[PDB]
Image (cartoon, coloured by chain):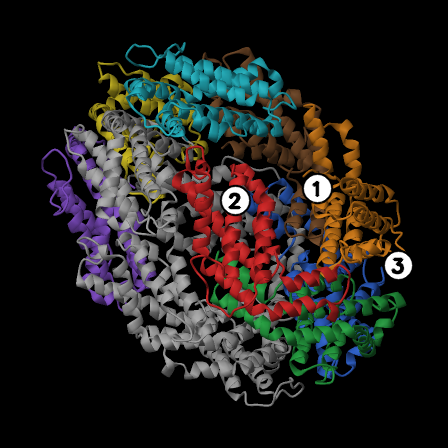
Chain colours: B green, D yellow, E blue, F brown, G purple, I red, J cyan, L orange
Amino acid sequence: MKSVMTTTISAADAAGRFPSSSDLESVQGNIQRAAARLEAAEKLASNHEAVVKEGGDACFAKYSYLKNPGEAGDSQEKVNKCYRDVDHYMRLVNYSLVVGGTGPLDEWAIAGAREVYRTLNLPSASYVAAFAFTRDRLCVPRDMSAQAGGEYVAALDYIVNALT
Amino acid sequence: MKSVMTTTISAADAAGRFPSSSDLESVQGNIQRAAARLEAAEKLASNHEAVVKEGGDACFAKYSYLKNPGEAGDSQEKVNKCYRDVDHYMRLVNYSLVVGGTGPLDEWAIAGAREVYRTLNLPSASYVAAFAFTRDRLCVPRDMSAQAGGEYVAALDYIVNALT
Amino acid sequence: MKSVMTTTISAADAAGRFPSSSDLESVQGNIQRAAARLEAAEKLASNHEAVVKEGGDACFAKYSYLKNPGEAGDSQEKVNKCYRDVDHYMRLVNYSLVVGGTGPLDEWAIAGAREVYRTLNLPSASYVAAFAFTRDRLCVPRDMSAQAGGEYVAALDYIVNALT
Amino acid sequence: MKSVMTTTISAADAAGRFPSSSDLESVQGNIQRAAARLEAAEKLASNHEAVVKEGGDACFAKYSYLKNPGEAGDSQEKVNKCYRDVDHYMRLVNYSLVVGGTGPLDEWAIAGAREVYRTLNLPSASYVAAFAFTRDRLCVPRDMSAQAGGEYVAALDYIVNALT
Amino acid sequence: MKSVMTTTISAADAAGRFPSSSDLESVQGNIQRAAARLEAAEKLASNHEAVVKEGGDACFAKYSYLKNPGEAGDSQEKVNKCYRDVDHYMRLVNYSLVVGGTGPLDEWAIAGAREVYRTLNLPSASYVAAFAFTRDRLCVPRDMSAQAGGEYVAALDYIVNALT
Amino acid sequence: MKSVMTTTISAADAAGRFPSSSDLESVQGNIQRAAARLEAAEKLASNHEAVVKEGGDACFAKYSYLKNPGEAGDSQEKVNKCYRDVDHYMRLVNYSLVVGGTGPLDEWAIAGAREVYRTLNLPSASYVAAFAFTRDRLCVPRDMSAQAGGEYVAALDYIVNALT
Amino acid sequence: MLDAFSRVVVNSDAKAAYVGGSDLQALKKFITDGNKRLDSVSFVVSNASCIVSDAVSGMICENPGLIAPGGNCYTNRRMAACLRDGEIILRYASYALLAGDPSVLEDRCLNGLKETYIALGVPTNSSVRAVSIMKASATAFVSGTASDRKMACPDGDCSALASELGSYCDRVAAAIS
Amino acid sequence: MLDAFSRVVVNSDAKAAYVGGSDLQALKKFITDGNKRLDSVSFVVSNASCIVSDAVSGMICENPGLIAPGGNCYTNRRMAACLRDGEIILRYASYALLAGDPSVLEDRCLNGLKETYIALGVPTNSSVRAVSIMKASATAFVSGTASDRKMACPDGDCSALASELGSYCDRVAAAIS
Amino acid sequence: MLDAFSRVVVNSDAKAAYVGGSDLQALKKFITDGNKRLDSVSFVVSNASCIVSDAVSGMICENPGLIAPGGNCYTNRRMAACLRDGEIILRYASYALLAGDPSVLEDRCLNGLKETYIALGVPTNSSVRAVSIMKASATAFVSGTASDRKMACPDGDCSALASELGSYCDRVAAAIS
Amino acid sequence: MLDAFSRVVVNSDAKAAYVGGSDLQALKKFITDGNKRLDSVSFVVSNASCIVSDAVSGMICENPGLIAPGGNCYTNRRMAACLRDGEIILRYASYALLAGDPSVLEDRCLNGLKETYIALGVPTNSSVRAVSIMKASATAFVSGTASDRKMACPDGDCSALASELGSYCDRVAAAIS
Amino acid sequence: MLDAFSRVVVNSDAKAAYVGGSDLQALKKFITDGNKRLDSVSFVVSNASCIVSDAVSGMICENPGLIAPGGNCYTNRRMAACLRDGEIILRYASYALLAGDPSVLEDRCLNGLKETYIALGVPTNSSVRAVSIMKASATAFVSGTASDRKMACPDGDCSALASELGSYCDRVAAAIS
Amino acid sequence: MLDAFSRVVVNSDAKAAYVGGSDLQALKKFITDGNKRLDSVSFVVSNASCIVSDAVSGMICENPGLIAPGGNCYTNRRMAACLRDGEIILRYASYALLAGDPSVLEDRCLNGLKETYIALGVPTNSSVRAVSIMKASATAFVSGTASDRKMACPDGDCSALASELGSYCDRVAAAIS
């Protein structure tokens, strides 16, 4: 689980070192930045159903062809799995904001995603559409503070880059 | 040169990653802590001649046997090298304070030190005596602020642990 | 370049062996199947422009969303590159039929395709649409002999599987 | 067991590939060539006792010194083991003809033969004499068809080259 | 346990060789030199308490600072352990003289000694003082024959070189 | 070149050690056994042509079939190359006795021998016949001292074992 | 690994017997049915992606627990590993069909597979189900009865090939769990 | 490995739940006391050599048989290896204290440790003693009650930190007992 | 590798000199504008895919010969390798921006790059062009002048950061020309 | 590596051209003459030991300086290594004959060969003669003109096959000279 | 590994005792009988090929089932490996005789041998027989009682060395039984 | 590697000549003076730590620029590596003295030493001085002329051995010069 703490500790362990000054300083930054990302995580946790709905809606709005026979969303159940997937990512966004690292997204969503989506005929651009919208939907200070908004957008940009 | 930045970058490089949230958070800690260790570095650089003298004096005060024939300080030129060595360590403490990592001490002072001191009959306890004194000589807020003092002590503790 | 001859020779070379019984037998099978695949290659080489056009048309007929702004077919130049791409594959199908192995397609089309198409927003299903049509358009004996049609379809299925 | 099928399968397995066109084309060679080598195998199986006798006879006829005290054939039991050894090889020749590869000869006769014959004072030239005779004894079309004879000779040539 | 026989056998085993001429020749040297080193070993075993006492006394006579508070000879028990350590080495010198190799000293005294003495504030020069005296104390032929004395001195020089 | 001195030095070098007690003892064995093997070497050097003559004669006396057409001694030049080969082994026996190790035999005679003799139809038992005779031909104390005779036989036994 | 021919010589070698005309009826039948066997392999391979994807999906849509938290197909990393396994199994099954012998499947795939799945915590009843659906679709493509695709070929009986391919799938199902 | 934060999301993921405000009270408190935690790690690390040496020496002075023939601290090679183990254990204990989670200690240090010690013949009770003494010294440096050194810091309560560090040492003892 | 701070240390060490007050004016400023630097890095990284893809495409649409037979981007294998190279270069460029020093770029990326490109036959002119376009786009995201996206941030001047990034890109072009 | 068919494809790909009926004349001829090519390879392989041994012995009998002290075939080790090289060269020549293309010989055998021989000190003039004798014997077995052995086959023209083998042997000598 | 001298050292070290005159009479006798021991090793090594071949042949000719199909000496490969094992066992036995201690035999040969033999299916009764015959012949060459060859040496008693070698062979039998 | 005896063998082998009585007088004397050679090796090795440390320190105290910033012995890491090289060189010189032949020194030490020193930029003149001082001290211990230590031995003439060792040091100097 990649975070500030686990990365520094892993580096120290690889060299067989006790935690030193640079390890301690790195953790101090985790302290400083925690408030912003925890605010973002809490806002997401309190309103994720509405956010997920908007994300999935944006996907099928942009790519209505998905509902055609033989396509990824040709049934209500398949469409439901699409919104479920968006919910999966956003919960991992919430996790990544709490952890302060892309760990939860890396291990639980991104790793092996290309193989899954390729094999199951799930166009990557459809996921991109959901999270590009989710990212661009935010504005400050309506939804959250500026630094909280920075964390929220950055985590979503991380997903979009991973998809592209 | 181990620091907050080089550690987190080499970690990202090993995984072929762009800088991410945890990398940026780590560097923020370098920002928060810089003032304290830069204060210690400045105070050291301004008054290092006096600190080094007390370091070397403390060594020979504790171990006068060094001045006996066949020992590490049986000549004035040898005694001068001893104070020179202490100055070299303290300059590396100054460097380590500036970098915010033990890099300078690791690569330039500690690496190969065992081999050198063993073959040249330079008892490690002598070096320890100089830095233990230098460390315990500190008092706050006379010499520096509390956090600056902590950095000062930590760097010297790092040396002592490396000698023991 | 994977073929009957290059596979058996490389296998012999790995074991440091002269060509033996099984090596010579394998090449005999290349002699027997040669006529079937060479016919498919010739028929393709003499009418590829008509084939490519139908493949490209099939792609955009199925996925008209490609011509929307920001998508892979939102300009005539991009549309032209798509037909160019179909021609690339079909030319490599011609090559693979002549060689009697998937070598040409493996090295010059499939390798690195996943990376390229994801970075450039080229949905694999669009390519699949072009070659699934090209595969199914064929009917024997109108276009070629039965065994020639088998080779033709097999090469296109290999591409389809490589995309899915 | 090296054959057309096992060679082409192991090659694909080493690359993690499904069987492709070149693999299938290789196996077609097994189909075309089987009639010739299965013929040769059948003739041998029907009359191996006579062929073996002639093989062992040619050995001791060319090297009468083997019957001298201290030599490999200085007793009836030892002589019987020699003809048995020739029968071993020829049975493995029968196997190699059925498999369509040198597999049976490689694993069960050739591998380790150098060490065994060296330790037990078994001159390799003696074995060569038996199979050189067996090879040259062939008369086409008297004993078998031309292609069957080609298989018969090739297997025996493989043994001779391995023995020299 | 490094000796003439163990070194010779290990070399033969690494190459998978039976013992050969050079192997047997090396062991002949173990026979010729045995008397000299066994004499030194016997003389040591008969009077080790007196030799060890002189060794320990020589250490504290040269480094009286050791009995200062905070130093390695802080108490009687610590002083007792110093003499004990000298006895340990000398018993291993006896072992090494019997074996005809530095094996006992290498495996049981030298290995890990640097890490141990470093952690426990045990100055290497103190051990050197004890064994250099022990070495220079030898008087030929008063204490032993010239060749026995050579073995005695050689083993102690080995320890000193390992300490410096 | 394998000998007492090269084996011990290679062993020391593998562990990065200076020569020590066991190394020096090993060489002492080379000093003690030297006179015997040098006696055998000189005796061989002073009358090798007669020794080689008897060796080659014994080979063809036992294996007269070699002079039959198509065999390894079916010409005058081939016969001369046989005696030449015997001379080459015996010269390397002389070298090995001087070296005090099987080095010369190993590098220059034995390495690659079975490959050459297999390729050239050179029966190994023919060589064995020459050296088994040479070994048993030795007369103590007619030809040399008992210990010199032991070195002589051991070297020839080494060749015989290397051929069987 | 062995094929259909080397299997015969292995059995004959145990009896130290030559392979004569009396032992060569099946191997003869193997040759004349060679083109059908090559078609069967091609038909499976040409639809490998559909076979694997449809089977793993079938396994999951029959057992929603696999994609729940704690489920063995939960997260994309596990799902991808499952899809990979399905592809691997189909690949070795196609190898066995090409060789006309199960040895390559047993040696290079099934050997130590159950032990591995137990150590990993892979639900073995679900694994069998994935193989079963793969058997259903693959044998259908060999028989030419696949609902949405018929492979072009001269009409005839491939029931023996389909049954043989199924037996290889049976071996997988028996080896795991 | 996990830290205090990823441990929460691991627990929450098992229930497929978002981490919300009602789940972050402890983690916000973790951040608030963050400077004290960094001091706790610094105070242990800065006295690592003394902590390890005194504890191993304490173990031996309590069990003299360890440095007798047949003892596991007999010869410099064994003593060095024991001092090495002491330093390693403290190092992973300090890792866990920094992360606020015992996972790095469990995964990279304690996993298998009992089995290797049994295989080597490393006495477990004496190992427990060394760890127990390290706990006494390390927690004292955290608590600021070390007899011969008091680290500079604002006066406050670090009993939670010291108790946490102590529990990490306890897990080591439990893992090999 | 070095950063902005260890670079000063290295330069001072060459003179056997302490780093004092006079030498810290630039480093204190590095700390002061630290948040802007973190923003500059985050902005480049968050648009990494767009930056690289657009640049390689720009290089190609300006020189279509690259994707014709005999072109160095012909076939998907070469195109992927070029896209990979573009991403790698930007990645090390972002490293340099985060560290405030080009050492990581010089030591781990550019070292021997020209020799490699000469060996493979990578056209230097097109390579420079890709870097040039990457410079324009990346520095635009730092400056906040990107045509189709403005990253949210407090209003202010980051011209120094963008100029620094541009210098890192220039170092890449210089090393391979 | 390339064969006769892949070489045509590589050349056609350079011109961005399909391979049509006009281009396939020689390749069709390659197929019709396929059985002769297989015979030629078999004839060489079946006499590999004689070809190599006779060539090396021929090289030596013409230049006894090779087996003198200082000679490069002196001692059994060098003699074995030379016999080894002869076999290897013939083996790669047989590979090229089977594929109908010199690429495997050039890529896996000839590339770097002169440099290693120069470094080792193996004489190039003697190496060339060893190849030339191999060329004489091997092509004779292909032409069915070998003085002490005629391989069974239907009578016909294999001069092109033999000349092709000769060209491969000539490439070996050329790359060495 | 240990020899006769380090064995005494190891035993003395267990009691923290110096090796003195009262402990050295057996080792002094070891030295004074050194030449006989060197002869004993030489006599075994000089007839190594005969000892191994004769024992393996004796093993087979007393139980012909070993070379029947399914027999563990069936095919040349198994026969070669069997001869190899016999040579290896004799080699480590010769090692032990030279060192005057069985440690090299126990540690570098016998350790795990029975387990690998059980796993491979090497019959233990046949192995014991091969060892038993090797013991007879090897001890014969040492005792100078071998029927077809007597090694030259000054007349004397080597019953002790013969018994020592015999005990080494007995160790092999016990380990695999 | 070669020793004094195998060197003679190599020369004799080059002319295909037996080593006879004429060519043996030097080797016979080599054996006669064998105990002196063993003493010479022992005297050097027993003072190895003093020889190396004194020579390296002498080099520094004669070349102050070595320990200035940028100096090749600046920092403990470089000083340690120089001390390591000194010990290494003396070790291979002692090997050569023991064998009575410089081959081991040439093959495993000096071989390629010059080009790594050039690549690393270690000063040649200072390296030569280190060797020349080592030569002074080492030959002094062989000659029994060392000022502060005389090694016990029968009084005699070891000038040839001292000259031989001195020649080995000169080979080192010439190689790195």
Q: Is residue E134 above or below residue J132?
A: below
Q: Is residue J116 left or right of residue E160?
A: left
Dot 3, how many residues are within 10 Å of its Cα: few (below 14), some (14-19), or many (20+)? few
User: Badge 3 is on which residue?
Assistant: L148
Can you give x and y, in whole percent of width and height, for residue L177 in the image? 79, 41
Type of the residue with mark 1? Glu
User: Badge 2 is on which residue?
Assistant: I129
Camera-side mark, 1 or 2: 2
Tell me which chain the residue with mark 3 is part of: L
Q: Quadrant of the C terminus of chain G?
A: bottom left
Distance CA(mark 3)–CA(mark 2): 72 Å
Q: Residue furthest left?
A: G156
Q: Is residue I160 left or right of residue D118?
A: right
Dot 2, how many residues are within 10 Å of its Cα: few (below 14), some (14-19), or many (20+)? some
User: Which type of secondary structure does the marked residue at label 3 adopt?
Assistant: loop
Distance CA(mark 3)–CA(mark 1): 37 Å
Which residue does the image show at 77% across and 60% down from the upper left? I15
Whether residue G140 appears in this view of the structure is yes
Q: Is residue D150 above or below residue B76?
A: above
Which residue does the image show at 53% across and 63% down from the upper left? I40
**Of pointers 3 and 1, the one earlier in the residue sequence:** 1
Can you give x and y, in whole percent of width and height, for residue E135 in the image? 80, 63
Can you give x and y, in whole percent of width and height, for residue F124 in the image? 49, 26
Q: Nearer the viewer, residue B102 or I73?
A: I73
Q: Which mark is residue G84?
A: none
